[PDB]
Image 1 (cartoon, rainbow over the protein chains, first blue to last red):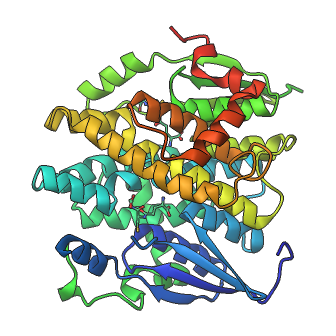
Image 2 (cartoon, chains in turn orange, yellow):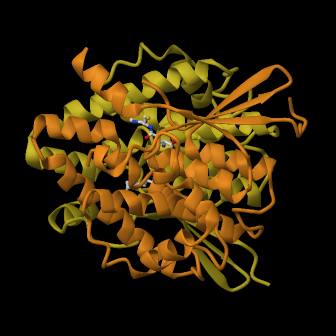
Length: 222
Length: 216
Ligand SMILES: N[C@@H](CCC(=O)N[C@@H](CS)C(=O)NCC(=O)O)C(=O)O
Ligand SMILES: N[C@@H](CCC(=O)N[C@@H](CS)C(=O)NCC(=O)O)C(=O)O
């Protein structure tokens, strides 16, 4: 089990516009790792549960007649970094590692949970419309923290001049900001980093619109 | 050469800060305690759209070789402590166990605690008084139910095997918060058993809110 077996096969349980799954798709793409895409239709399950809980992301690792199910984006990405150290998405110096993990956690723990689908559904059940106002408030708060923290240490990307785990968390969170109609004018460093990332093939590959389960534009809910 | 010094910005009852106090205590690391008037800070944030920047607790200030580093986010700080000061280890040696322990930690870090952040609960309360209590209770119970299941599959004496890990550093403060909101903990017997094993250890006793300089 503890040998770095080379014939591990990877299967990602993903939903096209899950920001949490997207982070893992970015880790996989940036490390050049092939994987099988297992679609989990979270919209269908939401509508079904309302009329009458799949975990996303889950990275299934198969080996020697054994399956491991890895959960939590940050745990999954830390596993990818330990198992496949090149190209590194955490730097080798300890201060930089702490900085990158902090930028990731600002999103992971400080922003995304406040706008997850269960949270938003419970908000708009009690007070109609208020979920999108709430999402904009908490996303803006998270992005303001990131703009300040990123500007100190960013080169072309969130940390220096190559992609790191911090970018894996930033890019999907900016997409959600746009989804909820948040003005990104106040985050110039984040916008710059987003543009740099968007031009790279691995980011293009991981984007919601390129995923097997992506609906056409005219069949996407807000 | 200026050897490394540690200062923790903490509030006695902050679960986020407590996690870091546990990492420090478990590793036998001395640190300067710097108390933050969190209640005054939160009152100001509430009246001003939570604009006050770089003001989250915990912050671990580390000075070495004439340079100061301000480490934020409990999980990032704890991972730094594990890398900087490896013994005693708070992560297991094997890749699978490390991923399990990090997932357990993140269930609390990202999946339970943010739902009961004072700002979240304040915004709920401003809209619908009383909603904050219902919400905190719902989300903490939901988090602990999922955590009970996950911890049971792999716990020994502690959350992961027979030694404390980062998972226990997240579990123990979250259970204290559950009690604060009046939640029955009977439905989480594995979590309770682990909590009791941790409570008997000197480092857990030292990190507890009641032992902190700013405890009233
Ligand atoms: N912190 C998790 C977030 C994943 C996530 O948001 N998952 C959804 C379910 S698909 C969730 O937990 N929603 C809130 C809940 O169901 O309690 C990660 O990074 O993997
Ligand atoms: N995910 C963060 C959570 C930190 C947190 O929630 N801090 C709060 C409670 S101590 C805080 O500083 N509140 C005051 C403020 O936001 O100004 C961590 O793990 O460090």
